[PDB]
Image (spheres, helix red, strand yellow):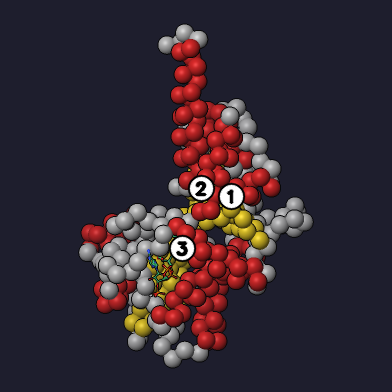
Amino acid sequence: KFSAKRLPSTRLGTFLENRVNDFLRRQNHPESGEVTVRVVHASDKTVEVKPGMKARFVDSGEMAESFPYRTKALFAFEEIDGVDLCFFGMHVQEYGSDCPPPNQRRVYISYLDSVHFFRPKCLRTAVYHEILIGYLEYVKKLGYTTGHIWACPPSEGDDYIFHCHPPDQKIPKPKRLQEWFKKMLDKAVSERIVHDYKDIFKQATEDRLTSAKELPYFEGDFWPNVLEESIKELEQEEEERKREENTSDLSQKLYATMEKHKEVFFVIRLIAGPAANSLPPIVDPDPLIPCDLMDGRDAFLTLARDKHLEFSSLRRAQWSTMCMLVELHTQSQD
Ligand SMILES: CC(=O)CSCCNC(=O)CCNC(=O)[C@H](O)C(C)(C)COP(=O)(O)OP(=O)(O)OC[C@H]1O[C@@H](n2cnc3c(N)ncnc32)[C@H](O)[C@@H]1OP(=O)(O)O
């Protein structure tokens, strides 16, 4: 059997699905089916400081040239009338205790995606929250101190993970997406999983950061590109001053930019104050899962496009869930 349940399991994937099914049992709703969570990719990577953060900090020896992270893809599946449906997927970036500041002990959500067919409707949002609470809960226990989310809906016609969302599934605007993360984080705060959370701006002022080198540097994320565009304009300014002399602050505009966009960037403190000082090293009990299809989001979108897998309705998304699963299974074999 190529079913989702039979996919090789993980501490992490298991933790998640256990949490959700407990929550589902407590709800005791006749239409809900069993949920399955599987990490289908885990591998070790680096993020490279782009040129010009490179120039200004790396070469100076003030900041490391790259940071190592593990990357992971996990999908949640619900069983509807005895048939697997993949309604949710997420890609995270985890930076262990073995990683250079600013990035150590931080997790980042690269992207997350869903298709709105989970049943019943009235539990869909709850379930996604639960998945997220549990993830934050898991990495906290491994000793990651801080989660990071950038609340960034996809551009129109663009797919984060699943190819061809249903024409009527609305895409939230930023304010709504913000409120949605807030409602999730409050629940994790009341459960004492999260200490507190703040926008990037407030957080950076509190941490009293004086320099861009201090800002966590993540793959695909906004700030490494902002800094680049900022040095780029910081350079054009210098060239403008160059002319005035007759020749052919970085952290200032960082703070300006941070303030302007602050609402859309979450910093989530899992462990604050005393504990984060001295911690045993981060030990991931789960194995590496090489999977070519699940490294980044583009492989599976290519496959989807190539093989015409759409998630555009419950019936297609199930068929797609089928192929996705078969592939994951045959691509797992010798
Ligand atoms: C960069 C990252 O990946 C991390 S930031 C997350 C951004 N990811 C995405 O935008 C992926 C595409 N979006 C999604 O998969 C979902 O929106 C996610 C983020 C999973 C949320 O799912 P939900 O829990 O259903 O929240 P949401 O979208 O806000 O939808 C709940 C209600 O919010 C309404 N709604 C959503 N977008 C709307 C809109 N644009 N206009 C009006 N109403 C909207 C929905 O019609 C829906 O109404 P109802 O069915 O309860 O009657």
- Residue 168, how many percent across, how many down? 29, 70
Instruction: Decide: few, some or many residues near mark 3? Use Cα within 10 Å; few <14, some 14-19, many ≥20.
Output: few
**Quadrant including the C terminus:** bottom left
Q: Amino acid at mark 2?
A: His
Q: What secondary structure is marked by label 3?
A: helix
Q: Residue at x 52, y 41 (%)?
A: 257
CA distance separating discs 1 and 3: 18 Å
CA distance separating discs 1 and 2: 9 Å
Residue at which label 2 appears? 261
Q: Amino acid at mark 3?
A: Arg
In screen coordinates, is 51 left or right of 100? left
In screen coordinates, is 137 left or right of 331? right
Instruction: Decide: few, some or many residues near mark 1? Use Cα within 10 Å; few <14, some 14-19, many ≥20.
Output: many
Residue at which label 3 appears? 176
- Residue 254, how many percent across, how many down? 55, 38
- Residue 48, how many percent across, how many down? 49, 40
Q: Residue at x 50, y 20 (%)?
A: 238
Contact between labelled residues 2 and 1, with CB atoms less than 8 Å apart: yes
Q: Residue at x 60, y 27 (%)?
A: 60
Sequence-wise, the earlier of marks 2 and 3 is 3
Residue at which label 1 appears? 200
Q: What secondary structure is marked by label 2?
A: helix
